[PDB]
Image (cartoon, rainbow, N blue to C red; front, side, top):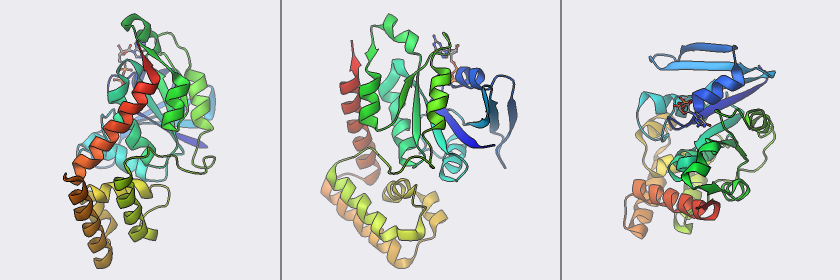
Length: 262
Ligand SMILES: Nc1nc2c(ncn2[C@@H]2O[C@H](COP(=O)(O)OP(=O)(O)O)[C@@H](O)[C@H]2O)c(=O)[nH]1
């Protein structure tokens, strides 16, 4: 209908429980084209102008699994206006790995910090506002068990969209990697969508074959990117894939130190 919201998080983060509260009996079950992966969507019960596109639970957008491919293709397309990232608050650091990839898509992320009621019993506290600040995304505490925060997070995701968010606030990595990403961006120009340019730049840096075949870049474009990779790999003395994963982990680690307590 009007605003299209992508619902995604790790498996066992409470996505289904949240999807059900939000949509009630306005659901639609189907098929992602060509594959047997279930496509589920629904209208927001309290606001039929908002549709929710549920996406398969994944730990990462990287793998060449059907589930991750579905998520990648949907989120690199133009259908979604907002990403509503369901996060398991009792397992924050591992959940944020996908989150970082989600922000890089350029579709504005809103986090539903789910399982907020489980924290206390585990002797765990989170500073929602501090977590929100360091990720550059809105964060709203939710619980599908106690049915709290649900309307609040939906409303926030609905007002944090591609049409209302001006500048992309991606996670900032080591200068040396940013220099490489920045240089790949220079080379790319119009060859990639402006919103998801950085996502494409990181993928080409990681030497993603699917993206490489998709983009069909020129001789000169492909050559410069090769030289950027080799020189940066040399600078770090690691392969590209490992540089990126280690930058994500360092960033996420910082963030969890700032926001988590015992
Ligand atoms: N205590 C508590 N349990 C939850 C919450 N959200 C979901 N669950 C439970 O977590 C389990 C997994 O929920 P689910 O919606 O299937 O997560 P999903 O695998 O991402 O779809 C179920 O037993 C839910 O009842 C929550 O906020 N608090």
